Length: 165
Image (cartoon, rainbow, N blue to C red; front, side, top):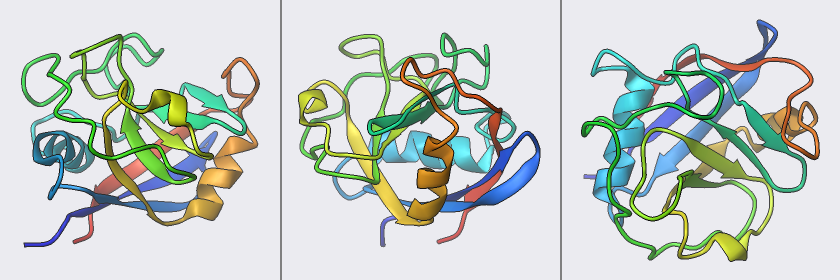
């Protein structure tokens, strides 16, 4: 095997921005990687396609994944609703890190965030499970639509998403 690669085609108020591809560390966090992969392909009948990045903070991160409530309070995993923190082997070492958002210990659903900088204070609190492979320039572009409190100036949506490799 080899770690899977998924992609997100980002749009700003419908206007295509570009593609961001991610390598999912299935070799270190198989359960967390699988949740993201399946939600990216939409194979379970629900997922990221059509959802938006509701919280974008410049110099920090781009958060999304709430396909149920579309406001940062919903979303769900492919294992029911919420699942345990698999492990904290990987750290938020720098820009491009893909990690799970949560509401405290063992509350992983579908929400995730892409770091635009090293965020060591999240180590041991959020499960790191992947990283940007291609399109970091697109993530930087998305970052320009965020604000200090996270509210986005325009709607940043996942026009399409799926698996490449």
